[PDB]
Length: 222
Length: 212
Image 1 (cartoon, helix red, strand yellow):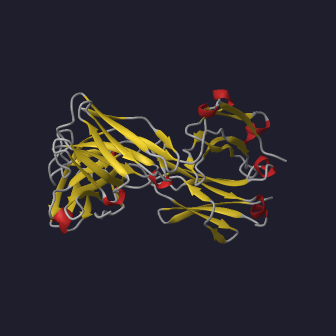
Image 2 (cartoon, one colour):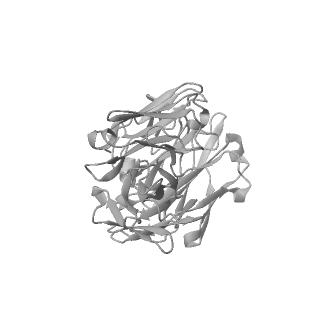
Image 3 (tube, chains in turn cyan, yellow):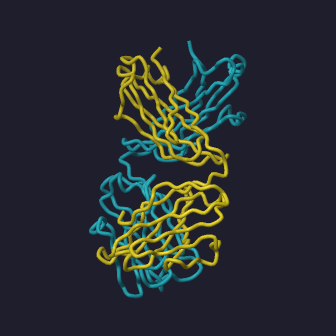
């Protein structure tokens, strides 16, 4: 048996989110189901549970009056609806099935998780800035070249170097979500310093949600 | 969290490790303990239930016990692949709800410690020209996977405008993270230098950049 959850969600502050959990490979109605969330870098947090056989639902105190857990007994799907969303609600939401009718039992089958992002931002392509070294190129020596992919929404953006020809020394870092509600990330390629006099380095940034493709030439300056 | 676990634990392959879970009379005192294991960017998996019972698919080197209002997970013969996050959980009778521990990051040193490689970039001229400024601090190839980042304007701590990512596993099995400091082009120019300081296993790597 597998628990399958609905896809990632982006929501505005004050709005509601409804995450779905289906048991594929037969009914999960005879067992308790819990919703557990995990805010980035934080631990597991129980939101509440439902046990349809008893027609009972329970909620963590901290979410009482804000979350509604339900089960469509006919379709074999459980749901979690969270209202009045703020940025503190940005997290991965898991459904998980207990081993029996009760919330005390181990949760032995977990859904894959659903990322919910709460942001007042709308779709926006990144500004891209070149990041150049000036004492890195010593002596020598390798040098770190980068491109800053600033203030985009929503995820995700892809980055390559020299239209894909350059893979050695590339590290693209995971995005930060800033308190503004927009993302930024950076890609760096480490190159031999000597190559900076003969080779051109260009970062190619593609942001599909906004149909933005940007090419930036990165080149130590002055 | 109503249940208390040590946030970080380390072990060497072949060695035994124990992760404790401290609870109260309303939860661990009265109810059975469950243990979950979670790898980065994926769902937890059930490891132990009913205090000491193991799912078929769990290696028998994993075991649990319950001691009054406390519970413990033991792993014998630590393998490199046990490097994960571990959570204990119990129903709580007073709360009428399930409670988890805060989690334990278990480090299995099947490789040497590595200090973070730190790359600090000043604002690009392009960004400064359009009247903005961002300091970018890139932190890679460190192991174990926790660091803390502190920013300095000259010799004094900056707190505001700092956005730091959580760490993430690389292909080569070490970790990376980044931290951003956003500022006005005037704040940037008024200081002789800014510094990104990254402390890893009680030792700091720093980099420094200047408006020159």
